[PDB]
Structures are given as structure tokens and as C-alpha cells.
Image (cartoon, rainbow over all chains, first blue to last red; front, side, top):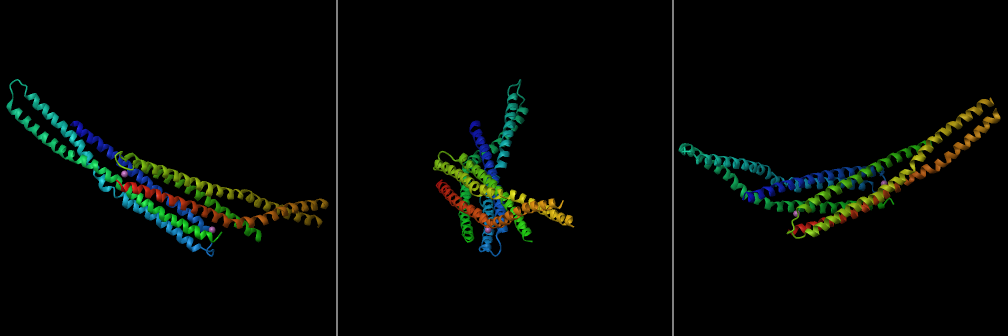
Length: 201
Length: 191
Ligand SMILES: [Xe]
Ligand SMILES: [Xe]
């Protein structure tokens, strides 16, 4: 039951470790998207550079390069708003639970100390009733302090653990939903450029 | 003159072409980086997917297909866009050398004429030199006068074909990826 609680603690550290990695990979994916965007803009700038203003389709190829720019921007901004910054509430939960767990640990040590002291007094050599009285009071106090920390963690850790499912499912549904749409809209731009370039064949 | 405007066009064609090669190479590197980051994200889903959630196997097949798609996309860009960019650019160095060399063979001939002119005011020999210098210059001149316009013309076809090839292979990549993301959204909706 130390054991029951230590399992919650081990689940909590795993949940914390996995949720940290998922964001970092999200962050890295985000930075990829931005660099793919910048590279695509330079590549389109090469086409614009050679495409003369009077050649048929020039203005339209331009329109398409600007739509491409906008599409990458919107994908990246939506990923940020809908998948990355939507994690805030959930991860925000962790720091203070971690802290409360280490504090529960110290209050348990304090409680164990006060038990040990109370115990040393019960095996005199005539009992010193007054010292017993104070040690008993310190024991009961340190037990209450420990037991409050303990009771709130015991309901809170299973609740958090269970919510990890929702978090993962929702984050990946937002990313996959956004991604389906981006790639759909993309392909249309590729098609539009292709039809313009058919004119110069 | 005419030949100097041809040389100018050529310098420009080489500059644009080199910039396109540099930018394509970057684009291919970015496509690889976006593949790898996407793959890692997928791996985070795979590592958290519980055995008692339905669709675990289907999610692994989707991720495997996703990896293969990205790999196919990058490889078609190499084959259809980049290695063709390289062949077109491979003709430029020798022509560039031949422009510089023609320039020198022109001064060579001018100074052989300015010398047959100078003596005539030993002459048996200078006229020999002038004929050799004329035959060597004019042989470079004619070859470049054909070749520079014909290279210049081919620029449009090379750009059109490069950018059409990209837009076709990208259309297919994006259409196919869109379907794979839809397949993953359907699995996830069922949790
Ligand atoms: Xe073009
Ligand atoms: Xe998930």
C-alpha cells in the first residue's frame, strides 16, 4: 500500500515522460512544416523568376504560389492552435503534482520520525508523562499533515492517469484531421499549376 | 553586338539554373526532414496505443504505409526533378570555357591582322599566321553562334518539364497521404 501508492507514482512519471516527448516531437514536426514551407517558397520563386510577365498563365502561376504560401501558413497556425497550445491544460496539471509527491515523501519521513521519538519514550525507565504528552501531540500532527497530502494524491493520480487516453486520442485526431485537409488542399494547388504549365508545352 | 547579348543570356540562364538546383536540393532535404518528424510523431502514437484499444494493428499498417509514401515521394523527386536538373546543368561548363576561349582567339586574330598590316607597310609568314588565326577563331564562332541560341531556347522546356514533373508527383503524394490520414482519423474516431 506503499506499493499501491508507488505504482501511481511510477505511472505518473511515465505519463509525464511520454507527454513530454509527444510535445517535443510535435514541436519538431512544427519546425519541419515551417522549413518545408520556406523551401517551397524559394522553389516557387525560381519559377516566378523565369516566367515572363507576358507568357500565358504568368499571373495565374503567381496566384497559385501565393495560395501555397497561405495554405502552409494556415496549416502551421492551426496545428499550433488546435493540437499544440490545446495541450496546455493537461500538461499544466503535472508540475504541481510532481511537487506534491516529493512533499508527501518528506511529510512521511517526518511522521516516521515522530513515531520513532514517541516510541523511545514509552520504554523508560519510569515514563516521563509530560514528554510523552508532547511527543504524542507531534505524532498526531505529523500524521494528519502526511495523511491530507496522501488522500488528495490518492484520488488525483488515478484520475490523471485515466485522462491520458483522452489527451492522446484528441491530439492525434486533431493532427490527422488537419493533415488530411492540408494535403487535400495541396493536391489541388499542384493540379492548378500543372494546368497552367500545360499552356507552355 | 549580337554575340555579346547571346553571352549575356547564357550567363543568366546559368545563374537561374544554378539557383534552381540549389533550391531543389534544399527542398528535397526539407521533404526528408518532414518525413522523419512525421515518422517520429507516428512512433509516439504507436508507443502509447494500448493493446485493449481496437485498431492497434490497423494503426501500425497505416504508419508503415505512411513511411513508404514519404520514401516514394523523395525518391521520385530525386529521379524526376533533381537528376534531370543535373543533366541540363552539365552542358554549361564546357560552353562557358568555349566562350572565354573564343574571346582569346578573337584577340589572337586581331593582333595577327594588326601585324600583317604593320609589316606590309617575313610577310610570307605573317599571312600564314593570319590565315591560321582566322580559321581557328571562325571555327569557334560558328559553333557557338549555333549553340548559344539553341541552348537559350531549351530553357523554357526545361523549366516547364521540371515544374510539371514536380506538380504531378506531388499531386499523387498529397492525394495518397490525405487518404492515409483519413484512414487514421477513422481508427481514432472509433476509440
Ligand atoms: Xe516557365
Ligand atoms: Xe491515440
